[PDB]
Image: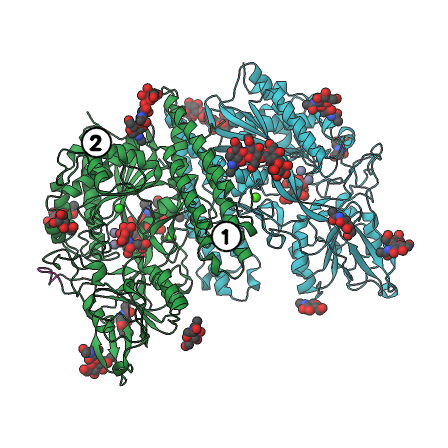
Chain colours: A green, B cyan
Amino acid sequence: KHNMKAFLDELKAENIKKFLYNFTQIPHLAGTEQNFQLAKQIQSQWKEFGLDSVELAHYDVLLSYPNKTHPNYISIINEDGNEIFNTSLFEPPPPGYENVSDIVPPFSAFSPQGMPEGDLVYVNYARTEDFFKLERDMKINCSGKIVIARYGKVFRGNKVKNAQLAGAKGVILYSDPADYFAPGVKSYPDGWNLPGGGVQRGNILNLNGAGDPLTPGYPANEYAYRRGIAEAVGLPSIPVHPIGYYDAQKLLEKMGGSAPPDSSWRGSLKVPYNVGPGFTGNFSTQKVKMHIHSTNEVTRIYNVIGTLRGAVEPDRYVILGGHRDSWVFGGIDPQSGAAVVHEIVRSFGTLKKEGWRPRRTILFASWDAAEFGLLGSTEWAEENSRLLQERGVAYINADSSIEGNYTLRVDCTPLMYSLVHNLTKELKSPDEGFEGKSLYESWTKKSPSPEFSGMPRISKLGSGNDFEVFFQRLGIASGRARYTKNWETNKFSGYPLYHSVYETYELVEKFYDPMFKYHLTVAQVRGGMVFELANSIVLPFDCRDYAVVLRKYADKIYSISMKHPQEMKTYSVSFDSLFSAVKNFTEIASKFSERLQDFDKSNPIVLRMMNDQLMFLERAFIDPLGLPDRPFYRHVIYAPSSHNKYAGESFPGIYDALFDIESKVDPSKAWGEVKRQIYVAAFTVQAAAETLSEVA
Amino acid sequence: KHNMKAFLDELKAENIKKFLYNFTQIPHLAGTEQNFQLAKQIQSQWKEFGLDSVELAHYDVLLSYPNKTHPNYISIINEDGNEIFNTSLFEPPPPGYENVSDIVPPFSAFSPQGMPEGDLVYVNYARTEDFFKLERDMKINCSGKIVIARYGKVFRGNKVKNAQLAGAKGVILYSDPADYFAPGVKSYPDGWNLPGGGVQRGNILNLNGAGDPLTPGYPANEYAYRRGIAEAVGLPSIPVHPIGYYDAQKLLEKMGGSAPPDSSWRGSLKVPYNVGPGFTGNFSTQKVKMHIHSTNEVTRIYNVIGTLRGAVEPDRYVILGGHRDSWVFGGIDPQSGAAVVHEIVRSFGTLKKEGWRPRRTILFASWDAAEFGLLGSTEWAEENSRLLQERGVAYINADSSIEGNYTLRVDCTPLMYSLVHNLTKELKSPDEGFEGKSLYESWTKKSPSPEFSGMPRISKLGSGNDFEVFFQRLGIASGRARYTKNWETNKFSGYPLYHSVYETYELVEKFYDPMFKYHLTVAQVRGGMVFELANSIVLPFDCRDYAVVLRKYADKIYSISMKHPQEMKTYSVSFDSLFSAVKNFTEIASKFSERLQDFDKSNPIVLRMMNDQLMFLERAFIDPLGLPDRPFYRHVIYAPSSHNKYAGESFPGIYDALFDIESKVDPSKAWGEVKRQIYVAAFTVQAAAETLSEVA
Ligand SMILES: *[C@@H]1O[C@H](CO)[C@@H](O[C@@H]2O[C@H](CO)[C@@H](O[C@@H]3O[C@H](CO)[C@@H](O)[C@H](O[C@H]4O[C@H](CO)[C@@H](O)[C@H](O)[C@@H]4O)[C@@H]3O)[C@H](O)[C@H]2NC(C)=O)[C@H](O)[C@H]1NC(C)=O
Ligand SMILES: *[C@@H]1O[C@H](CO)[C@@H](O[C@@H]2O[C@H](CO)[C@@H](O[C@@H]3O[C@H](CO)[C@@H](O)[C@H](O[C@H]4O[C@H](CO)[C@@H](O)[C@H](O)[C@@H]4O)[C@@H]3O)[C@H](O)[C@H]2NC(C)=O)[C@H](O)[C@H]1NC(C)=O
Ligand SMILES: *[C@@H]1O[C@H](CO)[C@@H](O[C@@H]2O[C@H](CO)[C@@H](O[C@@H]3O[C@H](CO)[C@@H](O)[C@H](O)[C@@H]3O)[C@H](O)[C@H]2NC(C)=O)[C@H](O)[C@H]1NC(C)=O
Ligand SMILES: *[C@@H]1O[C@H](CO)[C@@H](O[C@@H]2O[C@H](CO)[C@@H](O[C@@H]3O[C@H](CO)[C@@H](O)[C@H](O)[C@@H]3O)[C@H](O)[C@H]2NC(C)=O)[C@H](O)[C@H]1NC(C)=O
Ligand SMILES: *[C@@H]1O[C@H](CO)[C@@H](O[C@@H]2O[C@H](CO)[C@@H](O)[C@H](O)[C@H]2NC(C)=O)[C@H](O)[C@H]1NC(C)=O
Ligand SMILES: *[C@@H]1O[C@H](CO)[C@@H](O[C@@H]2O[C@H](CO)[C@@H](O)[C@H](O)[C@H]2NC(C)=O)[C@H](O)[C@H]1NC(C)=O
Ligand SMILES: *[C@@H]1O[C@H](CO)[C@@H](O[C@@H]2O[C@H](CO)[C@@H](O)[C@H](O)[C@H]2NC(C)=O)[C@H](O)[C@H]1NC(C)=O
Ligand SMILES: *[C@@H]1O[C@H](CO)[C@@H](O[C@@H]2O[C@H](CO)[C@@H](O)[C@H](O)[C@H]2NC(C)=O)[C@H](O)[C@H]1NC(C)=O
Ligand SMILES: O=C(O)CC[C@H](NC(=O)C(O)(CC(=O)O)CC(=O)O)C(=O)O
Ligand SMILES: O=C(O)CC[C@H](NC(=O)C(O)(CC(=O)O)CC(=O)O)C(=O)O
Ligand SMILES: *[C@@H]1O[C@H](CO)[C@@H](O)[C@H](O)[C@H]1NC(C)=O
Ligand SMILES: *[C@@H]1O[C@H](CO)[C@@H](O)[C@H](O)[C@H]1NC(C)=O
Ligand SMILES: *[C@@H]1O[C@H](CO)[C@@H](O)[C@H](O)[C@H]1NC(C)=O
Ligand SMILES: *[C@@H]1O[C@H](CO)[C@@H](O)[C@H](O)[C@H]1NC(C)=O
Ligand SMILES: *[C@@H]1O[C@H](CO)[C@@H](O)[C@H](O)[C@H]1NC(C)=O
Ligand SMILES: *[C@@H]1O[C@H](CO)[C@@H](O)[C@H](O)[C@H]1NC(C)=O
Ligand SMILES: [Ca+2]
Ligand SMILES: [Ca+2]
Ligand SMILES: [Cl-]
Ligand SMILES: [Cl-]
Ligand SMILES: [Zn+2]
Ligand SMILES: [Zn+2]
Ligand SMILES: [Zn+2]
Ligand SMILES: [Zn+2]
C-alpha cells in the first residue's frame, strides 16, 4: 500500500546525516555565489528525486555586508584619541575550518555606517520594561549615549528600536554567559557552549512583515520600482555591532554611575554591571568608539520551488518550506531543517516513482535570505498572493530541526492541534527511557500542557520565521515542529552557538544528535503533517479547537482590561460583544463538526464545499485593513508581539490599545481606541464563525 | 422544460406596472417609517413568491434630514440686512399629490449647518477644469466667496469638494435648462421636462467607497464603535443647498465682474452668466445669504435579503441587487428597477414551486440608503465580505430600469461581454421599427461600438451605484443594464426630473413606457443574465475579452504619458513591463480558453477548478493595499474617476499619477510615482494572468 506508513518508513536517519554534512562544508550566505550553487544543486536533486517541476524563483532585494577591506570594530578611546582596546575582527575559526574562505565576520546586518563616540550606558536586555525602569524609576537618560545591551529575551531588532526611541547614538550587542553558557558544559569544540570569542550575528530590522525593505507589498522582480533608502521599511538609524563576552568584559569592567537596580540586571561576568552613564573616575575621560562600514546593496536571491501535482485537487496547495541561507556553515540553522526537507522530498518522490500521487498538490520550498528579514519567502508570497489565498491549504515550516534533544516542540494554529495529537500517537518516541512508547507519550510527559492533564504543550505561532507571510499576512493555516531543550533545567536563551561560526556539522553530530534519531523524528512529524494535509479526504482541521482557544484569549484580554475598573465604568468599556462572538463561534463550530461527520460522504461538491469552509476558516481571521500602523500584520487573533517579534500575542489590537494605557495623556481617546479594537475583534470572530454556517 | 425560456416567458409587463404603481404612492425616504413598512412588505412577498429564506439586515448609519420647523432657504440680502428675495421652501407638488405628507423638501444631504453671507461667483459645472480656468487663466479667487454652480457633467460631491479646495464658504447648486430641459418637450405634468420650481435632491459626500461615514471598514451593527463627526469619512465642510432655475434666475441676473470666458460657460437662462465676483454697481452692496439647519443623525436602515438555494453549488452566489429608498416617490429612481426585481423574483419563484432550482445560489437584495452614499449595500458587503470574496460569482445591479426609451445601455466587466451579446441576440427588440428583430440588432444599430462594426457599445463600470462595493472593493464580476435616451439627439444630462418630486408613477406610465415593454425587456436582460450566471455549467465569462480591453487601456495610458517625451527620457519612464504583462495575459487567456473547451467535461473537480479560475479572475485585479489615499478602491483596472465618481477610469493609479503632472513642483518625484504605478499595474496584470495558468 501507498499510505502514510510507506511514506514514513522510507525516511532514513542516515540520509539526513549525509545531507546535513553535504550542506554545511562551506558558508551559504544569502546573495553569495556559494548559496546560488547550493540552490542549483537542490533544484537538480529534487528533479532527480521525482518532483514534477522544480524552478528557481529569484528576486533583487536589499542585503547588507561588511566591507572586506575596512573591517567593523569597537574601541575604548582615551582623552588623547588613542585606541587602547579593540574588539576582535573575526571569531577564532573552529578546528579544521581555519582555511575556509568567505567566513563573514560578525556584524549586525543593515546597520548604517558611522563612527559614533560617547559614554556607555548598560540597558540589560534592552526590553520595553528595561527602558521603563531606566527612565521612569532610575531617572537615567540614554540620549546621546552609546548603549550596550545583552542579547536575549526579545528579538534584537526590538532592542535597537527601543534604543533609538530612547535617543541612543549607537548599540553594542553582546552574549552574556548568563544567557548563552550552560553550567557544567564545555565550550566548542569540546562541548556545545559559547566560547568567549563567539559572536551572534543577526539582522536588526523592524520590518513588521514587509519583506524586502525597498518593495513593500509587491515582488522585487526585474521591473520593480524601489523606494529610496530614506523611505525604506524598517532600517535602523544608528550604528550597531555584536561582540562576544571576552570583548564585552573589557567594555563593561570600567562602568561607573548607578548600580544595577537588582540581580535581574546582572549577568555572570566578573564586573559590577553598573548602568552608567560613563566609566569610573580614573577612566571617566575615556570613551567608546564604534567603526561601522557595512553597506546595503540590492542583491539577487534564489528560492527553489518544487511541485508535486495532486491527483484529485491539484488546485489545493500544501506547502513545506524552510530557508537555505546561513550566516556561516548553518550546522543547525538552517541546514538541520533543510536536510530533513531534502529527505522528505526524496521519500515523497519514491512513492511518486511507484505511481502514487497525493490527493492535493504539495509545494516544497528552499527559501533564500531568511536571515536578512524573511525576504525570500515574503517576496515569493507577494508575487503569488492571489494563488495562495484562494488555493493555500496549509504551510508547514522547516527551519532548524533541533535546538536541543529533550523533547518535541510544536507551534501551530489551533486548526492543527488534533492532527498533531493523532500523528504523534502513531510515531515512536526516540527518547531514552521511552523505548516502545509513542512520541505523544514522551512529549506529554516532558512538556505537559499548562491547562489539560494528559495532553502536551502546543504554543502559538509568533514570527521571526518564514511562516510569517503565510500565516500573519495571508491567513493560511500554519505549523512548525522541532526538537528542543528542557526549559526548566536550562534558563539560558535559544542555544548557545546560535548564529556563530561554531554552528557546524560537528556540533550536531557530536553533541546534539549522533544517531540522527531526533532529526528522523522531526522528519516524521513534519512529513506526516504534510502527508495528512495533502491526502486526507476531509482536511484534518478541527474548528472546535479554535473555539476553545478564542475563549481563553477573550478571558485573558478581559483580565488585562479589568486592572482599570474605574476607567471601564467611566468610558463604558464592555467585552460583551467579544464574548457573544466567541459563544456564537463555539455553537456554530459544533454544528459544523456534526455536519462534517454526518454529511453525505458520496458527494464531491458537498465534500469540496466543506473542505473550502475548513480551508477558508484561518483566512477569515484576516482583516484587510491590517493592524494599526502595521499593514502586513493582518491576523486579528495572532500577531507578533510589538515588544518581541519572536513571541505570539493574542488579540494584539486590543492588547496594544491597553498597553501602558495608564500613561496616556488623553484617557478618553485611549479607552475609545480600546473600544474600537473590541468591536473589530468581535466582528472578526463573528464573521469567521459565519463562514462555517450553512452556506445558503 | 425548466430552462431560461420558461423563466423569460413567465415575466409580464403588467406585473411590473402593478408593482411600480404599488411602490410609488408614498415617499420611501431612507430611515423613515414608510420605507421600513415597504421593506416588510417586500420581505413578505418574496416569501410568498417562494424564496427559501428572506431576512431583513439592518444597520445604524449616519443619515441627514432638514429640520421640519426651521426650513432651509437662500436669500438676497441688502446693505441693511433685509431679505429681499427668498428661494422656495418646497417644490410645487404634482397634481393629486398636493395632500401627500412627508415629502422631504429639496436639500443637499450631509450639508453642515451655517448662515454664510457673501458675494457670488459662478463656476459653471464646478469641474476640475472649470476651476483651473477660473484660477489659472482668468485669475479669479473663490476664497471667502459663495459659489453658485450648475448641476451636470460630474457628481455633485466632486463639485462641493472642488469648491472647498478653492476656498469657497458655501455652494448653491442649480438645474440649468441647458442641461435639464429638452427642446420642444413640455414641463411636468404635461411632459417629461423639469419645471422652473423643480429641484434635484442629492447627497454631497465624497466617501470614496467607504459606506457609512462613521464605520469605514466594518458593519454599522449594534455594537459598532463610531468615529466622532470630526473624523467622519467624506462630509462636506461648507453649507450647500440645491435650487430650481426660477430661483437661480433671481440670483444670477445681477451678476457683475468678469464675462463668461466662452459659450460653454453660458446656460439657457436669460442672464449674462457673468462669473463675478459680486453683483453689478447698482446692487454691488447686496449679498447672498444661505440658511442651512439640516442635521446628521444615526438612523436605522433595512436591507431585504432573499435566498434561492442552489441545487449543486449552493456555496456560489449570484447576486441581483438594487435599492428601494427614494428621495420622494421614486417613480424612476429606484422603483422602476425594484419593480423589475420583484417580477424577476416572482418568475424564479414560479419555477421553484414546480420543483426547479438553479445550479448556484441566487441572492436577491433590496438595498436601503443608496441615496445617502450606497450605505445599505456597503454595510452588508462589509459584514459579509469573507463570504462574498470566496463565494461571489457575480453581481447584477437593478437601479432605474429606464432613463429614456431609445435603446439599451449596458455597463459591465469585460468578463460578461460575451454573455450580454449572446443573451440579447435571443431577446426580442421592443423598439418601433424593429418588430421581429433581436434586441442585439436594435441595440447595435442605435448604439454602435466605437471600435467594431456590427457590435454594440458596452461601457465600463464606474461608481455611484450599489455595484460599487462588490466590484471596486471586493472584485466580484459585475454588470448593469437599462433603457436609455439617444445621447446624440439629447445633449441634456441624465433625465430632467431626476431626484425631483415630479418623478412619479404617472411620469413613467404617461411619458416613458406606457406598455411597460421597455421595463419587460430590461427584466429579461437582467433576469437572463442572472439565470445564465446561476445555471450555466461553465461560468459564462470569456477571459479573452479582458485581454482585448487591457491592451486598449495600456495603449491609452501610454498615449497620455507620451505627451511628455522629454520627461520620459529624463526619468527613464517605460511602459514595457505593462505591455509585456498584457501580452502574457492574452497568451495565457487563449490557452485557458482552449482548456476550457477541451477539458474532460465528465469531471466535476476539474469543472469546479476551472469555474474557480473564472470566478477568481475578477478577484485577481484587486490590490489589497488599495489606491493611494483611497483604501476602499482596490480594483487596479477600474476605479471611479477622481474627478467624477459617476465615470469609470482605467489604470486609475497611473492616470492620477500623470494628471496635471506638468504642474508638480518636483518632477523627479512625480515621474517616480508614475513609474511606481506602472510597476503596480504590470505586476497586477501578470498576477491575474497567472491565475489562469495550469494550477500545478
Ligand atoms: C451572536 O449570535 C446571536 C444570534 O443568536 C446574535 O443575536 C443578535 O443580537 C442583536 C443584538 O446585538 C439583536 O439585535 C436586535 O434585532 C432586533 C430585530 O431583529 C431589533 O429590534 C433590536 O433593536 C432594538 O433593541 C436594541 C437593544 O436594546 C436597541 O438598541 C434598538 O434601538 C432597538 O430598539 C436589536 O437590533 C438580534 O436580534 C440578535 N439576533 C438574533 C437572531 O437573536 C448576536 O448578535 C451574535 N453576536 C455577535 C457579536 O454578532
Ligand atoms: C511575461 O512572460 C515572460 C515569460 O514568457 C516573462 O519573461 C521573463 O522575463 C524576465 C525579464 O523581466 C527574464 O528574467 C531573466 O531571468 C534569467 C534567469 O532565468 C536571468 O539571468 C536574467 O537576468 C540577467 O539579465 C538581466 C537583464 O539584462 C539583468 O538585469 C540581470 O542582472 C542578469 O544579468 C533575467 O532576470 C525571465 O527569464 C523571463 N522568463 C522566461 C521564462 O522567459 C516576462 O517577465 C513576463 N512579463 C511580466 C510583466 O511578468
Ligand atoms: C483524531 O483522532 C480522533 C480519534 O479517532 C478523530 O475523532 C474521531 O473521528 C471519527 C471519524 O469522523 C468519528 O467517528 C464517527 O463518529 C460518529 C458516531 O459517534 C459516526 O458518524 C461514525 O460512526 C464515525 O465512527 C469519531 O467519533 C471521532 N472520535 C472522537 C473521540 O472524536 C479525529 O477526527 C482525528 N482528528 C483528525 C484531524 O483527523
Ligand atoms: C456565446 O455564443 C458563442 C457562439 O455559440 C459561444 O461560442 C461557442 O462556444 C462553443 C461551446 O464551447 C464552441 O463549440 C466547441 O468548439 C470546438 C470546435 O471548434 C469543439 O470543442 C466542440 O465541437 C464545440 O462545438 C464554439 O466554437 C464557440 N463559437 C465561437 C464562434 O466562439 C460562446 O461560448 C458563448 N458565450 C458564452 C459566455 O456562453
Ligand atoms: C553535495 O552533494 C552533491 C550531489 O551528490 C555533490 O554534487 C555533485 O558533485 C559532483 C562532483 O563531485 C558532480 O559530478 C555532480 O554533478 C554534482 N551534482 C550536483 C547535483 O550538483 C556535491 O559535490 C556535494 N558537496 C559536498 C561539499 O560534498
Ligand atoms: C586598534 O586599531 C587601530 C586601527 O588599526 C590602531 O590604530 C592605528 O595604529 C597606527 C600606529 O600603531 C596609527 O598610525 C594609525 O593611524 C592608527 N589608527 C587609528 C584609527 O587610530 C590601534 O593601535 C589598535 N589598538 C590596539 C590596542 O590594538
Ligand atoms: C401594495 O401591495 C401590497 C401587497 O398586495 C398591499 O399590502 C397588503 O395590504 C392589505 C391591506 O389592504 C393587507 O391585507 C395585506 O396584509 C398587505 N400585504 C402585505 C404583504 O403587506 C399594499 O397595501 C399595497 N400598497 C399600495 C399603496 O397599494
Ligand atoms: C424671507 O424670509 C424671512 C424669514 O421668514 C423674512 O424675514 C422676516 O420677516 C419678518 C417681518 O416681515 C421679521 O420680523 C423677521 O424678523 C424676518 N426674519 C429675518 C431672518 O429677516 C423675509 O420677509 C422674507 N423675504 C421675502 C422677500 O419674502
Ligand atoms: O528577520 C527575522 O524576522 C528573523 C530572522 C532570523 N530568525 C531566526 O533565526 C529564528 O530561528 C526564528 C525562529 O525560529 O522563530 C530565531 C529564533 O527563534 O531564536 C533571526 O532571528 O535573526
Ligand atoms: O452616493 C453615491 O455615490 C451616488 C448615489 C446616487 N446615485 C444615483 O442616483 C445614480 O443613479 C447612480 C448611477 O446610476 O450610476 C446617479 C446617476 O447615474 O446619474 C446619487 O448620485 O445621488
Ligand atoms: C570599503 O571602504 C573604503 C573606505 O571608505 C571605500 O573607499 C570602499 O569603496 C568601500 N567598499 C564598499 C563596497 O563600500
Ligand atoms: C536627555 O539629554 C539631552 C541633553 O544632551 C536632552 O536634550 C534631552 O532632552 C534629555 N531627555 C530628557 C528626557 O531629559
Ligand atoms: C543531548 O542529550 C543528552 C541529554 O541527557 C546530553 O548528553 C546533552 O546535554 C544533550 N545535548 C544538548 C546539546 O542538549
Ligand atoms: C430645529 O431648529 C431649532 C432652532 O435652532 C432647534 O431648537 C431644534 O432643536 C431643531 N431640531 C433639530 C432636530 O435639530
Ligand atoms: C484669495 O483671497 C484671500 C483674501 O481674503 C486670501 O487670503 C487668499 O490667500 C487668496 N488666494 C489667492 C490664491 O490669491
Ligand atoms: C418615448 O418614446 C418616444 C420616442 O420617439 C417619444 O414620444 C418620447 O420622447 C420618449 N420619451 C422619453 C421620456 O424619452
Ligand atoms: Ca516586496
Ligand atoms: Ca461601515
Ligand atoms: Cl521551524
Ligand atoms: Cl442599474
Ligand atoms: Zn533559521
Ligand atoms: Zn538564523
Ligand atoms: Zn437610484
Ligand atoms: Zn438616486
Residue A97 covered by magenta stretch: yes
Foreground residue among B516 and A195: A195
Judged by depth in the image, the label closer to the viewer, 2 or 1, is: 2
Residue B280 picture quarter? bottom right
The magenta segment is A93-99
Q: Are labels 2 and 1 on one chain?
A: no
What's the distance in space between the residues labelled 2 and 1, CA to CA?
62 Å
Residue to which mark 2 is pinned:
A426
Q: Main secondary structure of the magenta part?
A: loop
Going by the numbered disc 1, the residue's amino acid type is Tyr
In the picture as drawn, the residue positioned furthest to the front comes out as A566
Q: Which label is found at residue B674?
A: none
Q: Is residue A260 left or right of residue B74?
A: left
Going by the numbered disc 2, the residue's amino acid type is Glu
Residue B507 covered by magenta stretch: no
Residue A413 spot, x, y in % from top left? 34, 40
Q: Is residue B187 left or right of residue B140?
A: right
Q: Tell me the element at label 2.
A: helix
Which quadrant, please, contains the C terminus of chain B?
top left
Residue appearing at x 38%, y 30% in the figure:
A611
Work out whether A487 lies above or below B333. below
